[PDB]
Every structure is written in C-alpha cells, then in structure tokens.
Image 1: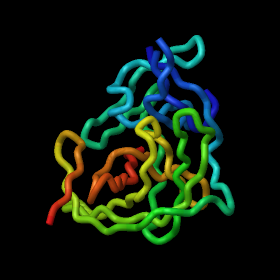
Image 2: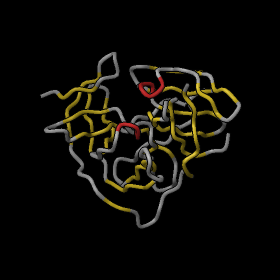
Image 3: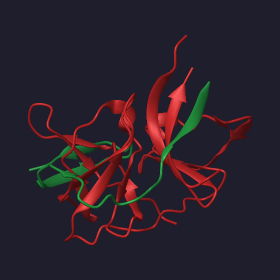
Length: 39
Length: 151
C-alpha cells in the first residue's frame, strides 16, 4: 500500500535558509542501525 | 523514473512516511521508512534490490547509486520534503559523529518524521547522504547522521 510521488529536483538553491548548529559528538552504531552517545 | 526527490506515501487517508531519491533509475531511501516493502510508481511496481539495516538504507530496481560524500569543511543543504509542504532547501554546516570507524558528518536539524530519507546535498548538487538516522543529545535536540551507502 506504499507509493511514491515526485516532489522536486535535486538542486542546490543559492541563498537558501541557513540554520542549525554543528555539534561534535562521540557516537556508537550497533547492529540494529541505532546510534547512541558514548563518553 | 525521472531523477529527483520523492515522497513515500502509504494507504483510509494517505500518510507520508518518508522521502527518497530517484537517480539513474534506482530509488534510494532509508530502510526504516519502507522496511523493504515493494513500492508502487504509477501503474508500475518497484521491488527492493539491496538493503542493510545497519546502514539503515535500501535501494529499489538496482544497486545503490549515490556515492558523493561531505568534504568535511563546506556547508551542505538538506532538501527537506516535509509532509504537506513543498520541498525546501535548508543550508547548514554539519557537525560530526566521531566513531571507532571514523567520522561521519551530521546535521543538527529536526524535521517531522515523514521527512526521513530527504537528501543532503553538496555545493555541486550531488547527494552526499540521506536524512533521518541519528541521536538526541538533550531534550529532543535531534542530530541526524549524513547516511551514505556504497555505490
């Protein structure tokens, strides 16, 4: 019951909205694909 | 068939469960979006071809085609396709997931769950990974790995 619908082109948009931090994080990735924080 | 970014919808009412990338005739999304189920595209059907729960990635109709990677320096753009919104580009400088197997770029952007699978782009417009597998650091501050496969 799952279908796809086109949503746009894959393009860089010059002068786009800019936001978000850039944290540096120690992480572990387990067999289930789950990331977790490590110290 | 045409290249681009796509909504992944499910059928009362239609819900958007994810996003994916069509490129070189192969559809790319994250595994947790579809769990590997077949997809319909028009009258046609798209069948899973490769998948990996650890990478949380799946490709349809062919092998994974995206191989661009973050350069570790420049800003990137999340091409977020939120449910009920038109596609929009969010520019950001990625953080880093430091792991035993090396560094992975990560974007500190928190969009609705139906946006999982949205592509992250480099300055040349190449898909460097997909959005929506990551971690929470403190009070629902979600950070997504820039998840890329192997071509």
